[PDB]
Amino acid sequence: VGSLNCIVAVSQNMGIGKNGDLPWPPLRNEFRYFQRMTTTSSVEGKQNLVIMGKKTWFSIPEKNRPLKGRINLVLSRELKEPPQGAHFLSRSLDDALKLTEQPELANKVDMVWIVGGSSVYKEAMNHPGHLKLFVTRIMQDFESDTFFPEIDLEKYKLLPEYPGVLSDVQEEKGIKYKFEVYEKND
Ligand SMILES: NC(=O)C1=CN([C@@H]2O[C@H](COP(=O)(O)OP(=O)(O)OC[C@H]3O[C@@H](n4cnc5c(N)ncnc54)[C@H](OP(=O)(O)O)[C@@H]3O)[C@@H](O)[C@H]2O)C=CC1
Ligand SMILES: COc1cc(Cc2c[nH+]c(N)nc2N)cc(OC)c1OC
Image 1: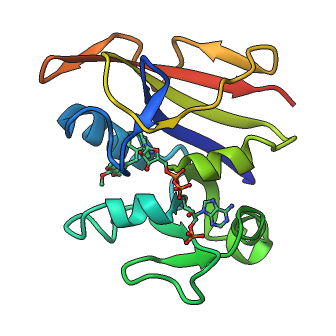
Image 2: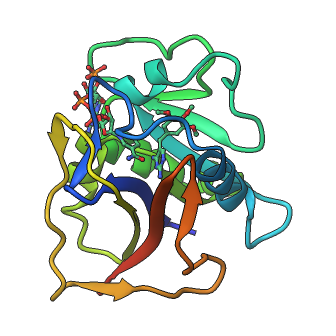
Image 3: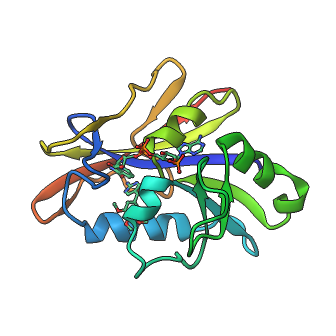
């Protein structure tokens, strides 16, 4: 309860994506791993609440939306009503987090998962409480427009091998990448 988990991928050049798209082509392993990973709930009888940005939402194909298995939440400050296909909408991060933290929703929601974008990470990056951050390093040079902020090792712990997550380097379509785990101390 009241737990926040961050999960995002980044290129070896500290890249996240260009024009709202990942530097590397669609990865069947990265896509399945992400879904299967989030789908893997620790507590039975509960649902996971994920939050995505406007860019991320519009970037996700309708073929997958709404994403079954988990509740999709979009963060929009300009929009008044939630977008078609979305489960809920929040004006700000504090609003979405506060609502999910409230007993009213706490009964239905237990843990939260951040699925981008950088804007959401930036706001959450200033969280005082304990928070988890999953960074995937892609061993390959690719073009990117947005850069990811450097994580403080003094505050964040480098977890190369964590239970549930694979440590071995995967390879798809000639693209090698590794999953890294980061934990922030309170
Ligand atoms: N390697 C990877 O796994 C992944 C990589 N990426 C890359 O990273 C990029 C991340 O894009 P992103 O940083 O979101 O792009 P932008 O900052 O350009 O847009 C994000 C939008 O999200 C909404 N938003 C974000 N934070 C808040 C907040 N606190 N309150 C209200 N609304 C908020 C806003 O929408 P409104 O305009 O409606 O206010 C904002 O315009 C992707 O485009 C992609 O290139 C993205 C996902 C995964
Ligand atoms: C869950 O589906 C998608 C999720 C994401 C975001 C995303 C991708 N990969 C990783 N490692 N973290 C993320 N937050 C980007 C996508 O396309 C760019 C998706 O396809 C719909």
